[PDB]
Length: 263
Image 1 (cartoon, rainbow, N blue to C red):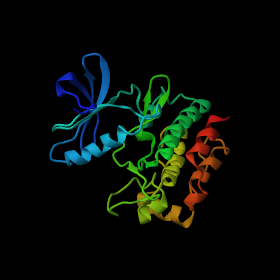
Image 2: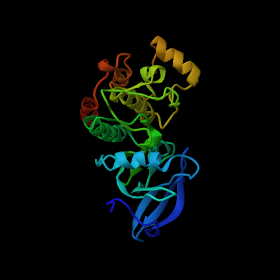
Image 3: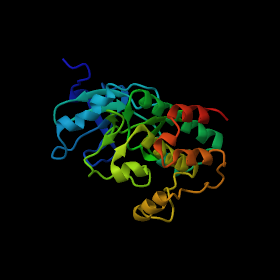
Image 4: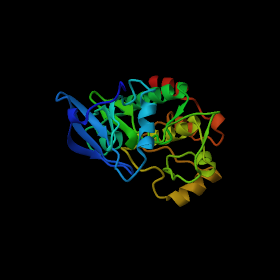
């Protein structure tokens, strides 16, 4: 029988943690002693086969800076049981005073963690496609992990041409991806670049006064974001590095991981 399969009896949902277009994520315990997170699938929403494509990828990706899969309940409603992160979303962790009081050297640290996780996915020939503050979960001791592999794909030749329909976060998504549906690890690099922006401005929304419509034209014409306040030019140059038009010209997460790891 399946090694990851588990009996819905051993799961005791206790609190809603978040939502999704295909399901609601909950907090609950497994076998009465381990805190877990359950990513359920709303019945009339998506195919059990599809929902499960995320779990399939999760069983193939194991890194410490990546939310780990604990089990799966393959019968409707589907369940994806994973590691529970105390602090919650990086986005909301910054939007307060706990992680908000956080000083640079500390923020740079968490960033280095996200690069390490990305570097792994890089080597694994995977693509996240939805990299950003809200999808980064924070655990105890300022630990940061990448979560939500709903749109993650194993890179074929080198990119992924979506159905040219799905709508992605215009502000975090690279231009060649949202205009040609040409996604690559380099596209996440662009997104990493915008995450720095967030992680550096207390979880502010990228491209302040503009809208997905506007942001689409400036970036295109070659205009990027300016160095955020109390933000070194040093790592803003890192951000403009991540926002280059030619993806080949953008750095690799390996580089990125070390760069932030050194200061």
